Length: 89
Length: 89
Image (tube, rainbow over all chains, first blue to last red; front, side, top):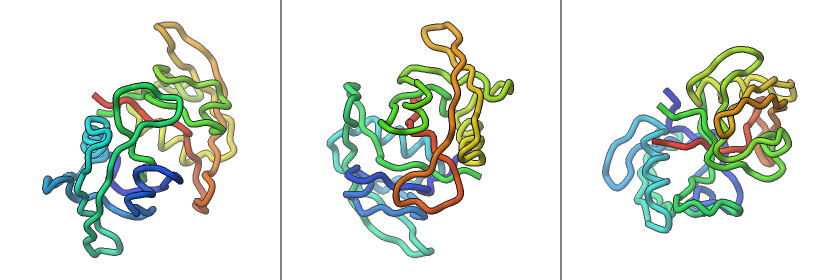
């Protein structure tokens, strides 16, 4: 139900470094289409330090960006984080 | 599908101030039961600067905490943020 559309981008995060912005919609990761935030988050979690090739939509137009999921300060889990919050209905 | 269980808590956020920790499960907000992260996030979004009464579960035991959703630096939308990321399957 949560839409793959960014509400907020955190500073010095994978998302800011990738050039993501509030309002951006995640459309494809590594060529694979997605429609749910959880799909995107699962991929991010599973891929710390791996380049994900993103196709996003901004203002109805496509952009190709690279996102590399990172750890978070204070978190020692072997997972990647986005650095952004999603929009909710 | 995303579980109302925290994977990470951000510093100087509503969640850290509330005393929330990774692994905590959100069980009730203002007496109302929830089972999905989106339900919790909707409430947070809708309630900037309003005290939400949280019942959480940590290690299988209930705790009562207060959470006051806040804005994020650089975001001028009239909404509240949690200050945390959820666990995903």
